[PDB]
Amino acid sequence: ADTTITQNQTGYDNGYFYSFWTDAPGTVSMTLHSGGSYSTQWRNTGNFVAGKGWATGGRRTVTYNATFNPSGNAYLALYGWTRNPLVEYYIVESWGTYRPTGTYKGTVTTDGGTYDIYETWRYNAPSIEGTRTFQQFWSVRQQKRTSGTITVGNHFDAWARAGLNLGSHDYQILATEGYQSSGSSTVTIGS
Figure (tube, rainbow, N blue to C red):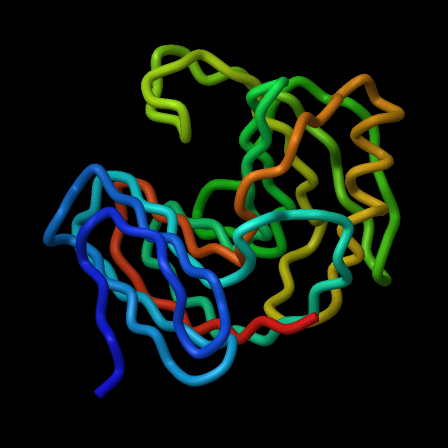
């Protein structure tokens, strides 16, 4: 009965927005469960990002619970996009074998944890507007965790103070992202 998604799509399930994107169709799937719940599983994937959340991001206080079992490079993060300026952003709660990094921008302490702030650039890569070159803003927890509250505003403000300006918000989801790895996850979001 639960809907399983395997091709690039955005839509709604049990009252929540969901997004699914991969450049390696057939290597990853996302299953939509009740309420704000979803699961994913992947094997020898290229790159994918999937999760439930909202069509329009903002300064929400997100609460979540998840089981994250990556076998290689993967992230568990609040993820989203903005336009004017075009920015892909991440609030990384947990990761696989690779901790995301970039140009160091300082730190932010929020929701009982300390996150390092980084900036990176993606060149000629897929984006919400197509193939573009754009900035990536990151808040990466110093210690992994798979449950808790994310006070999005605190991260947004810290980014702003570090010179990382966001534009008009597009979607925002508690995403599972994988890169050249295998694994699985189950995540439940709320606000």
